[PDB]
Image (cartoon, rainbow, N blue to C red):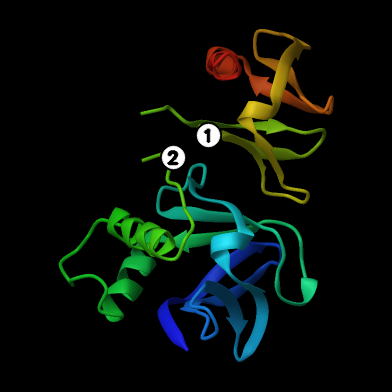
């Protein structure tokens, strides 16, 4: 089989929480790309034909941890229907650079992790899908809030909103948002309820009051 690249000892959070080895390879059958996540020789997760099965994929910042990055991917199905929740992995930036150097993908004098991101994004286009990098000409933002008693991170991306990363991880299409309603408004926080075109309602609470303008602008985009 044609292996394109690998990363050893990646910290996967969803749809399982385990350190796993990532292998990106092309199927011998039709050349379509595959990702598999290994523990020893055991394929814990595999997603085939990424060119058809990845619904969205993005690099996302880890709040308060600039040395790390998330790679987030949603998929139509996986090997043996083992899981449905989105793939969320944490990459250590410097480790990724070190691994890419040892695979001969980057020169030893390269110091910018964004060169790793560039490589990975180009491997996706070469194989028929797209991994975005919205935080590196539209302004994306993220913030901490609750979806009840549990804190999470709300990401506002050009085409999607994500609330992560405890189960169930929420992904909404921006174009599906019908309205926003503000409630429990105080000097410190407000609550926001997003209603989609299908009439469904998504309630977020305890958002810092300073986030109002960005959120209101976002929903008014277009």
The reply, left or right, for residue 153 in relation to residue 122 is right
Q: Are marks 2 and 1 in contact (CB under 8 Å)?
A: yes
| Near-viewer residue (85 or 190) | 85
Residue at 28%, 58% in the rendered image: 115
Residue at 56%, 18% in the rendered image: 211
Relative image position of residue 132 (x, y in whole percent): 45, 47
Eyeballing the image, is 119 above or below 28?
Answer: above
Q: Which quadrant of the figure has residue 155?
A: top right
Q: Residue furthest bottom?
A: 41
Eyeballing the image, is 15 above or below 63?
Answer: below
The local crowd at label 1, few if under 14, some if 14 to 19, many if 20 or more residues have their Cα within 10 Å, is many
Relative image position of residue 127 (x, y in whole percent): 44, 66
**Residue marked by disc 2:** 134
| Near-viewer residue (158 or 14) | 158
Q: Residue furthest front?
A: 30
Q: Secondary structure at mark 1?
A: loop
The local crowd at label 2, few if under 14, some if 14 to 19, many if 20 or more residues have their Cα within 10 Å, is some
Residue at 65%, 8% in the rendered image: 187
Instruction: Count the labels in the image.
Output: 2
Relative image position of residue 16 (x, y in whole percent): 71, 67
Q: Earlier in the sequence, mark 2 or mark 1?
A: 2
Q: CA distance from mark 2 to mark 1?
A: 7 Å
The reply, left or right, for residue 93 in relation to residue 181 is left
**Residue marked by disc 1:** 157
Q: Which quadrant of the figure has residue 198?
A: top right
Q: Secondary structure at mark 2?
A: loop
Eyeballing the image, is 55 above or below 78?
Answer: above
Residue at 73%, 12% in the rendered image: 182
In the rendered structure, find residue 45 and report the number of the disc placed on it: none
Relative image position of residue 222 (x, y in whole percent): 53, 16
């Amino acid at each position: 089989t044609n292996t394109i690249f690998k990363l050893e000892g990646v910290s996967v959070l969803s749809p399982l929480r385990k350190k796993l080895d990532l292998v990106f390879y092309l199927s011998n059958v039709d050349g379509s790309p595959v990702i598999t996540l290994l523990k020893g020789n055991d394929r814990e997760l595999s997603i085939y034909q990424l060119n058809k099965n990845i619904k969205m994929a993005s690099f996302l910042p880890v709040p308060e941890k600039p040395n790390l990055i998330y790679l987030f991917m949603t998929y139509t199905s996986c090997e043996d229907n083992k899981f449905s929740e989105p793939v969320v992995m944490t990459l250590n930036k410097e480790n990724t650079l070190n691994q890419f150097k040892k695979l001969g993908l980057l020169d030893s004098n390269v110091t910018d992790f964004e060169k790793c991101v560039e490589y990975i994004r180009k491997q996706a286009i070469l194989t028929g899908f797209k991994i975005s990098n919205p935080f590196v000409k539209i302004n994306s933002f993220h913030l901490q809030c609750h979806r009840g008693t549990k804190e999470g991170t709300l990401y506002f991306l050009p085409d999607h909103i994500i609330f992560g990363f405890k189960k169930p991880i929420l992904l909404l299409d921006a174009s599906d948002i019908e309205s926003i309603t503000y409630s429990s408004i105080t000097r410190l926080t407000f609550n926001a309820s997003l209603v989609t075109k299908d009439g469904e309602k998504y309630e977020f609470s305890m958002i810092d009051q300073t986030e109002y303008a960005k959120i209101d602008d976002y929903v008014k985009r277009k």
